[PDB]
Image 1: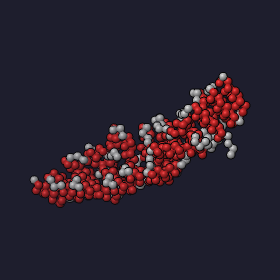
Image 2: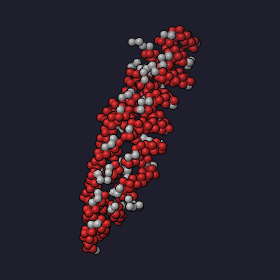
Image 3: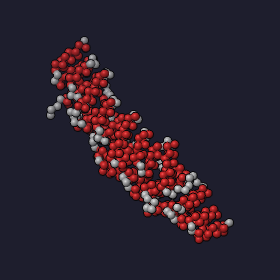
Image 4: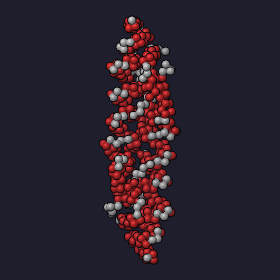
Length: 244
Length: 243
């Protein structure tokens, strides 16, 4: 694992001449934050100097493109709510950061998950964002997100597993997905959606839109199973016509 | 962004023959007042058949070895408590899982943070393990975990940041680290530990153990700064002997 104090570790592993200067400055500092150059003494001096050292180390992690290490270091200082607010602003929120957010209370975790969710939408991870909105008990909001971004399959699975079977939302997903597929010429899959919404007539009709013989036969058999025999006959007729 | 429903998605993308048989099988099912081979139909039928499909999909993920996607599917079923217990028993906990644990209650997150720390130690990620112990307000346990694993540098950084200057645990860290540095011959670094513990008298002695002209010299000036003038002279005259 990568160390969180590499700069200070380097200045502690240098010449014996350099080490001896540290003892004398530190000794004078103890007789009472005195030094300026030797920031790495904050490990042995006082908290105000330790924080100085940490800030230098954190900023150093940033300049190497390691914001994860910056954030993991700022937790030690104790300002979790401040790190999260900064992490959200920078778009560097992560699972590890959200895992520790409840340390400030349930209300800070709620804020963090929403923040991490909004950010995850920008990062093109709508399914992961959907899971996090589920974690804060926002099932409808999570489902509307996936639907809005054309993740109909995953949205239906979330809506079917959490909502009562007759929820108009669950039905609207089948419809909303069906129309879209109908639009783009996927009549077979569209029928499955209309069937899922308990709309058997429309399931048979969209399947008839393809026009071929196989589609019209199955569409007829589908209408017979359901009990719309008048339509099943009408589609059975249209099936035999194509074969001529 | 790997899909969470590979197997079912694959079956839905098949020849027109297959989707037509699906429609027939599906129409029969919906017409029910009171199927198996087509597990992918659970998305369109009922919750009981959906769960069956998810379980099949989760089984496929565990065969693939991608448990983070196995975890997403179980959150959908509303089985977060179950999958947390499962991932703990198998050592598959993640930051993702702990980030969602509060969904099952504040005390489940508190439980998951502990099990994730115990797991991170097994995997020898002690600084991360300690950081997560700080999230549940266990400072002394995080400091003792790092100390006991020879992470004195990080153990002091946390103690100094969270504990008070006169906390006995902070002094014992400095002394404990110095004892190890002195045992290995790192005499200059050992002095700073003793100085960090407000043991200037013992810090000058250790710096003299080195024995060369520069060590005794600095050790003598160090004792002078403190006010241990009796000792300062003793070392500055041994400094002369070397010269």
